[PDB]
Amino acid sequence: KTAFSNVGRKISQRVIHLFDEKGNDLGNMHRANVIRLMDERDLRLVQRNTSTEPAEYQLMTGLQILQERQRLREMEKANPKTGPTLRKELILSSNIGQHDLDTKTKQIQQWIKKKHLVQITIKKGKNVDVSENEMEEIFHQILQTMPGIATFSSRPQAVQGGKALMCVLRALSKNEEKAYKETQETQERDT
Amino acid sequence: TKFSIYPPIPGEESSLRWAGKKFEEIPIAHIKASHNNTQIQVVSASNEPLAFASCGTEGFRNAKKGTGIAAQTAGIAAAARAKQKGVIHIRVVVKGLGPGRLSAMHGLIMGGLEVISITDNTPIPHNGCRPRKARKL
């Protein structure tokens, strides 16, 4: 998270690859020499590219710093590209009541619907002996509620010496969805 | 004579001069000490903008702007743009009870400006608009 704003007269790094306001490459210069050009022409320096190992800073007028972000405000509006995926977690118990399982199963539908990743964990019920046969039958029982909407990303594993099972769900991908749709029609319509 | 703390009224003629200028002619340094920022704007007696500086314009972000070091830095930056235009004596009009209320005044003194008066113009209503509800934090 950054913004196209002036860095000020406090530079952390001694050597900077300074750039002119008109786009000319002034070349690497000492940190002190950078501030002299900020006063001689009353200009503010903005870090254009952080990624490069050599520091890159461009000195431009305040009006030029307004037009720049005014364009980053349109490019993102025109073509927004926010793809981070949130991860949600649930920790159930083998002996979880159905009423609580329908409440937690409806919460997974809201997350899936928001393209989130739902990590579900199941643990042995309080002083209850149970294997992994019916302890893994809760995932299939939750996934069934979301037939086409959801699919496994990971699969059940013995996270803690078998006393727990962990799975991760995701919203079905567009292509996968279309494939599911196609299959659904054949079973009923063709018959 | 003695020394009064009350500002010299314009109408009545006095002998208090600063570089040959009356109290009315001296430029004004408007300081807005907010809770998360501190804006400074120097103007003349005829409302002509001479300099503007703020913590945001000095390269501070978010919670660094609501400090006394950022307000002082903005005072030094506004006292360097106005000192090139022939400004020495100023009338401070502080507005707000923020952290950079007095720190910006020190930065103006660390820029070559001499303060002759301190005016407080913090907006106080005689009940007018209703503020936001109290918070539970």
Image (cartoon, coloured by chain):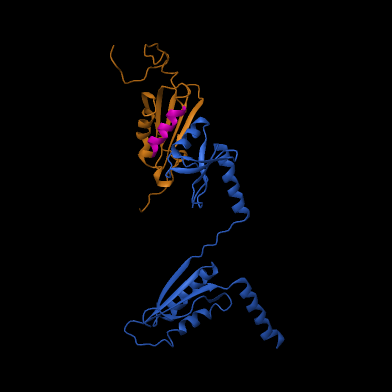
Chain colours: A blue, B orange
Q: Height in image: B133 above or below B25?
A: below
Res. B135 visible in picture: yes
B85 drawn magenta: no
The image shows residue A27 at horizontal and vertical percentages of: 53, 41
| Quadrant for the N terminus of chain B in the image | top left
**Residue A136, quarter of the rendered image:** bottom left
Magenta-drawn stretch contains B75:
yes
Q: Is residue B9 left or right of residue A111?
A: left
Q: Closer to the camera, B10 or A56?
A: A56
Q: Which residues are magenta?
A: B70-81
Seen in the picture, residue A175 relative to A42 is either above or below; the reply is below
Coordinates of residue A109 in the picture (x, y in percent): 52, 72
- Locate residue A116, reporting x and y percent: 51, 68
Name the foreground residue: A160 vs B34.
A160
Coordinates of residue A42 in the picture (x, y in percent): 51, 32
Q: Main secondary structure of the magenta part?
A: helix
Out of A39 and A162, give the one closest to the viewer: A39
